[PDB]
Image 1: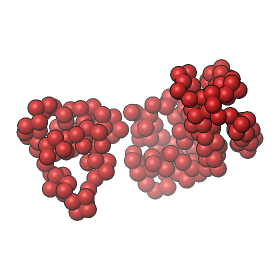
Image 2: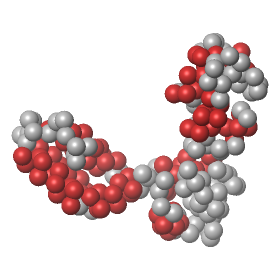
Image 3: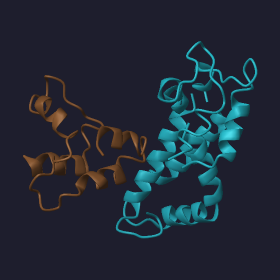
Image 4: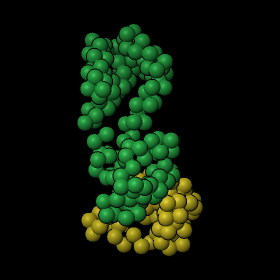
Length: 136
Length: 70
C-alpha cells in the first residue's frame, strides 16, 4: 500500500511538473485536497510517527528492552495527537510480553520517502500557485 | 547582557535546548545565573521567566522548567 501510495503521489507530482505559474490544474488539485482533507489529516497523523524511539529514555519506566504503556501513554500525548491514536499505538506495539511496549520494531512504520513526496507536493503547490490563501 | 540572555531564551531557549559547554563559551558562567531569583535585575520587563515557562515549558515539564527557574 505504501508502494502504491508512493507511486500515486508520484503521478500527482508528474502532473505538476508542467505547472509553474498559478496553474489551473494544480489549483484543482488543491481543491480536491480540500475535499479530501480529512484523509490527509489521517495520513499525516500517521506521518507523525520512528518518533517513538524518543519515548524509550524521555519517559523511561524500565529500560530493559521493555516499558509499560503508561509513561509514554501520557508523555508526548501530554503536551497534540489524539490519545485514540495512542491506544492505536498500543496495538502497534502488538502488546509485547504483555503491558510492556517493544522498541525498535516501532521504527519500521520505509514509508519515509512517501512523506517526502507529499511534502514536495505541498511545498511545490505553494509555489505552483503563489501568493494564495486556501492552499496555505 | 540581561537583555541578551533574556531575548535568547525568549526566542531560542538555548538552555532549554542549544546549551553551551566550555564551547559557546559565554554561556558557561551564564548557566548558573538563571537559577537565581534576581536574574532579571534591570530589564524592565522583568517577568520574562514566566514567559519562558509559558513557551518552552509545554515541551517539557511545566514545573521542570521551573525546576530550572522559578
